[PDB]
Amino acid sequence: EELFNALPQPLQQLSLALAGEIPLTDHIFEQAASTWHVQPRSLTYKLLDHIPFATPVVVPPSIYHSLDWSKCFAVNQDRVERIPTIDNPDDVYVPNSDIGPLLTSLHTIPDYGFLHPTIENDATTLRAERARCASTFYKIASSQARQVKLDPIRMLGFLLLVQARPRVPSGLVTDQPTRRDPTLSPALHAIWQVMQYYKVAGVYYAPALVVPSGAIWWIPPPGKRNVVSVQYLLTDLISLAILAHMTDMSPTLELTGVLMYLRAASSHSYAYTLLQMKSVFPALSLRSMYRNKGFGGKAPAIEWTEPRSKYKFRWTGVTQLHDGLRPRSPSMDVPTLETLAKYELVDIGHTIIRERNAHPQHNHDSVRFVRDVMALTSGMYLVRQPTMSVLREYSQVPDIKDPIPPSAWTGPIGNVRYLLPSVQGPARHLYDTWRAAARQIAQDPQWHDPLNQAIMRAQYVTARGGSSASLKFALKVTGIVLPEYDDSKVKKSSKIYQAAQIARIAFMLLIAAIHAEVTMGIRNQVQRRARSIMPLNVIQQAISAPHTLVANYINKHMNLSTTSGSVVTDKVIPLILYASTPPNTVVNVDIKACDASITYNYFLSVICGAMHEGFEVGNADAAFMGVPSTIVSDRRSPVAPYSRPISGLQTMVQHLADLYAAGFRYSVSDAFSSGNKFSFPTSTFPSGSTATSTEHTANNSTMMEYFLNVHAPSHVKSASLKRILTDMTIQRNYVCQGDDGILLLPHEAASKISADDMNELLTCLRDYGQLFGWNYDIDWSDTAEYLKLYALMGCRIPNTSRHPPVGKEYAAPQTDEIWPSLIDIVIGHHLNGVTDVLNWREWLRFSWAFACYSSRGGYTNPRGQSFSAQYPWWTFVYLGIPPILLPGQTPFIHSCYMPPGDQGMFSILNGWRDWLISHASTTLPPLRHNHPVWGLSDVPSLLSQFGVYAGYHAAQHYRRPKPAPETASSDSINQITSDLTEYLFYDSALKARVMKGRYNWERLSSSLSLNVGSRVPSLFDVPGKWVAAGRDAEKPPPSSVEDMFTSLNRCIRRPTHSFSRLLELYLRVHVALGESIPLAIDPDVPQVAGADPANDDHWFKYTCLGDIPSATRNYFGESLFVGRVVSGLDVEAVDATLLRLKILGAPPEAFIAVLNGIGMSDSEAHQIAGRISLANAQLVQIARVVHLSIPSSWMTLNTGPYIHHHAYDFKPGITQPSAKSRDKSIWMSPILKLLCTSYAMTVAGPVRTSIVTEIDGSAAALSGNLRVWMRDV
Amino acid sequence: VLDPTVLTNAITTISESTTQTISPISEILRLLQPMGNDYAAFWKCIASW
């Protein structure tokens, strides 16, 4: 095309690669990456002008008609700068005004400009109503432009680079030339129509150019203005132009989306208008599909596994659809078109409904219509003021329609009161569930165990990054010397700086004076560069310890989360698919603002009274975690008040009632508004704290249980619905996690329920939360939504708008990163386009374009003015992205489900190996010696020519600057580390375990004589793990970055042209693929939306394997052989330590030395070591000792039976008998079967039966050589 | 029509412990790996009659 002609010649040379015409050598990857950086970014929009094209979209000139920002911002109490709401009381986001007068010119680039420094100077010195008002708007408006990964200026550049040349047709017959043209896309046309305003000489100035410090805005010419809505409009169009070519969207559906963004840019406060229509497109398609007459298709017949608490699921065939299976629920059409009439977008509604009625049945084409319209929702991360993010949404107090009377409480027992039995509303079932769950902890002897107490203190440090240092406030009652620890360079956050100083002072001399106003929010100073964040003090989390534990007991028997890395893809996804099936219709119960719905006015007074009566069981004279027993003042009896001894477990509830009733002191110290700073209480829990938000899960199942059994079977007026509500049970019909959860209807009258009966149910359920202030976000759209994931007739609907192609959440005004951390954002950006299925070739074409810009880095040092790096092309191959073309074969045969690592590099060097031996037997001299896996052909010289070894070591090399102070100098290192060691080692019994562990292991390191100085995860790695997890967020010095930078170029250019000693041993194994395995599902049934036969690669994998993970003998390791660890030690690193020693034939003292290292008792270390075995272990868990693992891209598949009994260690008629793993097939076959699947999932097309053909050595030679490797590790 | 996999499929499903040094399943397939490189030798026996 003429678009390809307009590209630069090195940039043309990479579009030939992305099309698949030529292999992508490293020289094309270097020159074109250098072409991106030296190019002015404004030249990218000139390339959009080089396409002559037309489509019916007109960008109005009414976008540029702006408001005045100073009319939109003012000052209120405590001298805070904020946005007064103009129209509606949630008008809080960025107003669309000119950034023009607020910016000065920039010294380096005269065309752009940052903030005028007179406004920057005085607003930190003198708090004005103009300058402080200006810097609030500027830093917020720059932040919403900063919400991208890199510039959308370049993200449009990769998309035009992919669309320059069409992809070449591979020999796989399921590919198609794409139906989409760039000429027909109104997304690209609206960007060109906007950019006609932004040129003065045909140069196309971008309105912003987001430097990694922050966005820098374009200066306006005289007569024209630069409003802030355009850069946000451009980002949303580029976010839509990328996805629509990846979702293969119709051009009549982009225009449906584009006209909403142009309407919101025409309106004022663009992000607020875009927020009010955040649920239009799912309501027009996903929430309402099949309400018409003609309905049919095929649906999965998923059955609940009849032991109900197991939460297991099995795909048990197909279900042909009919008009009794279409949703009885009313359509969401009438409430949605009224919302579109508020913004004059009623033609957007009638466009979808005309196209939705073209899909009467449930097919592959129908679910693609759902995800195409769900791609039209903007996934733009809205940023308001972090002051105003808390001043409104963390300020809403609930409305209790039925408050508890004061006569319903007993006399006080210290601070707390008990609930009288005379009141029997839903508060009683709240009071009686939290009481009996509190009884099962004073009985439970899991505590007063030194390892269990060490896990809980590890749980507060590791899980969240912490907020403040209120021990500077907690010197008010106890004289502390207060070490500032500037002689240790460590960050002063709540992770390390608090808990190390806690090891000196006991809790009882501290818990009486914990109540602080700068409890949380900012690092012990009222102005910094950080945002006000959620977690609180570690000793006020320690006084909140029983409230976590009683909430854990409620969620134990109901919510078997099992604390696994695969719990969304094992439990949530099949429940999503078991819901929305034509047998059962569901009510996806959501509880909005649940964190701001738990107060001491109703909830926290009941549970603290329930825990205190619940902890009355057991010993009243018993300490707990260092809090002793104490005297309470009983006032229940009016005639006999007295002093009672209460336990330490009841002592914590006395201080917790004082802390919950005073509230939670959020202190806002954001760096966005110029110096607004105030701490204030709230009744709002922290949001992301999973150890605290499990209390919301503890109330979600509990309050639904009183609804389904007592409240609604008595309150509802429908006599027919009382028959349904009789046998509903939350152990069968309700699943919760967090605030949201699925309600299930009983299988007898599930799909045959009247919608008039369901509307009377949900009216009573919405009125049921009015007794608590719980605003239920009930939906009745006959679709599933458990944790922000969707379904339609048992087809998973990947929300493409949830993971944006351009967007990225930044809670900081800066990115706070050195350059090569962008590469780890690339791989996460790639796999989100693989999980949420897209056009897998075009997404892989887009990924190599997007990764090519992330290959060069330039550092600015005042000492050294020049730094330039270059990762090779093969770096991204090791990290997970499959290559589009190898030299010597056809393109787009490597699947996106390829593993990363050595496991992925094995897969490419297997099918491409036959070319590598033949192409190196010619054109290269043979080896002087002999090589085991390639013979006399000089393949590792040829692999050195393509830079295979270059990108291999460049990917394995680290990409984050290590800190500069070490222990070899005269630095005082162990000031804060050894005090944190004293925090973890409180009891002398647990210290006697770990000193026994390292003494026995270092005795058995040399006596057993296999390793020396090898890393074994002891508990002394955990202060090394914690303190190094504090300096990773600290900005590194330029001495550390350049040392990290120079180590990159030394790692790339070094002559080590060998792989690791596992991949050198993997390449002996030659696997080969026979016919395709017989089918798991019927491919007429859509498993995941987007996996049609057009998107062929994702279509076979969900058809050959299936998306319901079959719980087998293996079940991909939900068990991890150590049920509880100190948080900081990876159990992945523990099973890869014990099972090696089981293979190596270690004495049982070697196991006990490892288990005493992690803190297990001597009674426990024997009892784990005999329990672990090589046969009782699982086939995935055996392969993890050789660093082979299931990738994240396989987690949504049913890899269970395929690794079990389709992958061959030994297919007896086909293979050669040199690969007989005799007496080693207990542990070599999990390696051999998983290397079979490592290559089966790499080849495109259907999943073939994989067979080990031969090993170049013996299989005994490989079992010997991995045994040499397992001794070295 | 000769389809030599049927003799292979009848042999390759005979069970054997792999712990032995000799696999008699291996040695009879070793005697039949090139398969004589042809199958006209059967018909040359018949045409010689």
Image: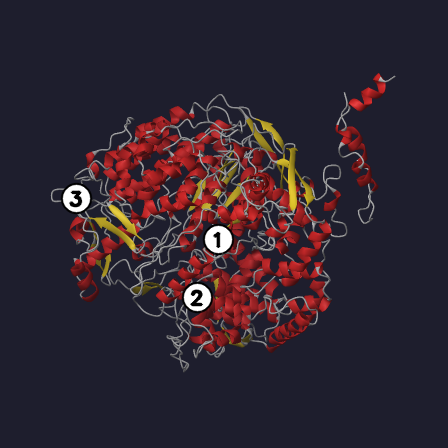
Find residue A1040 and report its horizontal and vertical position in percent.
39, 65
Label 2 sits on a secondary structure element that is: loop
Crowdedness near tag 3: few (<14), some (14–19) or many (≥20) residues, C-alpha within 10 Å: many
Residue A225's disc is: 3
- The C terminus of chain A lies in which quarter of the figure? bottom right
The earlier-in-sequence mark between 1 and 2 is 1
Give the residue type that dot 3 points to.
Answer: Arg
A19 or A1025, nearer to the observer: A19
| B39, above or below A651, in the image | above
| A631, above or below A1012, in the image | below
For residue A1006, side relative to residue A756 (left or right): right
Give the image quarter of residue A487. bottom left
A360 or A1225, nearer to the observer: A1225
Q: Which residue is mark 1?
A: A955
**Numbered label tally:** 3
- The N terminus of chain A lies in which quarter of the figure? top left
- Label 1 and label 2: CA atoms lie apart by 24 Å
Structure colour scheme: secondary structure
A711 or A780, nearer to the observer: A780
Image mark 3: chain: A
Give the image quarter of residue A449. bottom right
Give the residue type that dot 2 points to.
Answer: Gly
Q: Residue at x 75, y 39 (%)?
A: A1212
Residue A1079 appearing in the image? yes
Image mark 2: chain: A
Give the residue type that dot 1 points to.
Answer: Ala
A45 or A233, nearer to the observer: A45
For residue A286, side relative to residue A1206 (left or right): left
The earlier-in-sequence mark between 3 and 1 is 3
Find residue A101 and report its horizontal and vertical position in percent.
15, 51
Image mark 1: chain: A
Does the CB distance between marks 3 and 2 fall below 8 Å?
no
